[PDB]
Image (cartoon, rainbow, N blue to C red; front, top):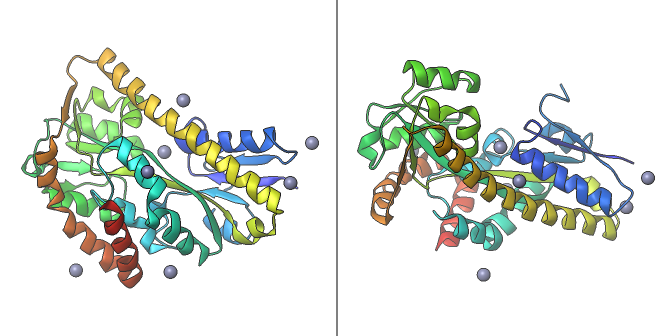
Length: 304
Ligand SMILES: [Zn+2]
Ligand SMILES: [Zn+2]
Ligand SMILES: [Zn+2]
Ligand SMILES: [Zn+2]
Ligand SMILES: [Zn+2]
Ligand SMILES: [Zn+2]
Ligand SMILES: [Zn+2]
């Protein structure tokens, strides 16, 4: 009767914004109700696979255990460097729009939408202009072999640290830098202790929303259409929020601190960085093999 929807984050976060806008559209255009579940509220991917949940929002990067190839988004420069062309990419990419749903299908999930949450931004105690600037810098990222490899290849020393300890580790010098979307940078106030921002353009934290396949396929052709329409709605709304949360975050960071610097890379500096990417692709294929090869190939085709 009621539809169960779980995501990875807390209220107000991007995935929750997408979720609520999805819930909104369904309830505004039907009698169905979407029961949302934020983090911890269920004790989740396996649940959706088993039909216990109907909808789930989980980032392909943290789905390595069920779908190794889903981690592909952690390869630096996998996708275009500018916000405009990445959006073009999510729209036209045969890899995103045709291959990926196949991968989730093999695990009993109807893939509804993949979307960028925002551009990765590096903060450090110095401005970063070349790979060499990463040398001897203990960088904290989200935990994944591909994220550590990106920075191992950049010259840096990957340094694990629970999220809630990241601020204090930047202050003490336990770490010298980290990467996060500008809005987590602003909101966490990381710029207060790590004032130099660099837009490297190498990563876009990509997430994904899907349904139980048996559930989705058991839906009337009208309900299937409703879900698709609701996902499209959640997508457009979410994209605009992201663009707008970005600039608002960049602005209020500058409103808060006079020590914050912003470094952006020209076409040629970025190129120096892309030369390091193959080391990460290899690590990706080492982890995923022939399926990874299949996926990675489409992604390279699509970027051309
Ligand atoms: Zn998020
Ligand atoms: Zn009713
Ligand atoms: Zn076009
Ligand atoms: Zn497969
Ligand atoms: Zn219905
Ligand atoms: Zn908004
Ligand atoms: Zn190897």
